[PDB]
Amino acid sequence: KLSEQLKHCNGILKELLSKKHAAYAWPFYKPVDASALGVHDYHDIIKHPMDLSTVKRKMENRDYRDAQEFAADVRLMFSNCYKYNPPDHDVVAMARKLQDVFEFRYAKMP
Ligand SMILES: CC[C@@H](C(=O)OC)[C@@H]1N=C(c2ccc(Cl)cc2)c2c(sc(C)c2C)-n2c(C)nnc21
């Protein structure tokens, strides 16, 4: 079973995956498929890929040791997006909007 802080984190994850954020969260649902997107240098630039399905798998299987490990993975997912893409890219605006949800909810962790 999950700790109280990791239960709060699981609630954040549920919110990030919910329909109310779907219009900007959907790029982050699954691992970036660099070959399908035709982005041949993605894994040259991004050393440690991350996405919400991976965070969800780790949460369900109780892989996270604590809330800070969860937060590191979520921030890594957003960081990779910023690292690869230019600042005016549509996916960067989606990432910042979803990250604002995460950061506000994470700051309210009891
Ligand atoms: C791989 C580098 C980016 C790119 O393809 O170069 C233009 C890429 N962009 C898109 C993207 C493009 C436009 C919109 Cl509106 C939404 C998403 C995207 C993902 S995952 C996904 C299923 C998609 C459609 N992605 C994440 C996450 N980080 N970078 C990206």
Image (cartoon, rainbow, N blue to C red):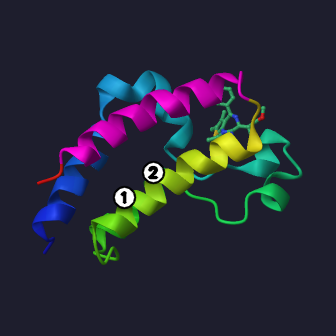
Secondary structure character of the magenta stretch overall: helix
Please, which residue is most extreme toward the right here? 40
Residue at screen point 56% across, 36% down: 27
Hey, what amino acid is under mark 2? Leu
The amino acid at mark 1 is Lys
**For mark 1, does the 10 Å Cα neighbourhood hold few (<14), some (14 to 19), or many (20 or more) residues?**
some
Note whether 102 is above or below 72 in the view shown: above
* Residue at x-position 77% and y-position 49%: 34
Q: Which residues are magenta?
A: 87-108
| Number of marks in the rendered image | 2
The residue under label 1 is 56
* Camera-nearest residue between 62 and 82: 82
- Whether residue 32 sits left or right of residue 36 in the image: it is left
| Image quadrant containing the N terminus | bottom left
Ligand 1 is found in the corner quadrant, namely: top right
Q: Is residue 91 magenta?
A: yes
Asked if the residue under mark 2 is in contact with the one under mark 1, i.e. CB atoms within 8 Å, the reply is yes
Please say if 45 is above or below 24: below
Q: Disc number at residue 87?
A: none
Mark 1–mark 2 Cα distance, whole angstroms, equals 6 Å
User: Residue 98 versus residue 61: which sits nearer the camera?
Assistant: 98
| In the rendered image, the vertical position of residue 12 relative to residue 1, given as above or below | above
Q: Does 34 appear above or below 44?
A: above
**Magenta span has 60?**
no
Residue at 80 percent of width and 56 percent of height: 45
Residue under numbered circle 2 = 52
Residue 17 shows in the view: no
The answer to whether residue 96 of the structure is visible from this angle is yes
What x and y, as percent, mark residue 88? 71, 21
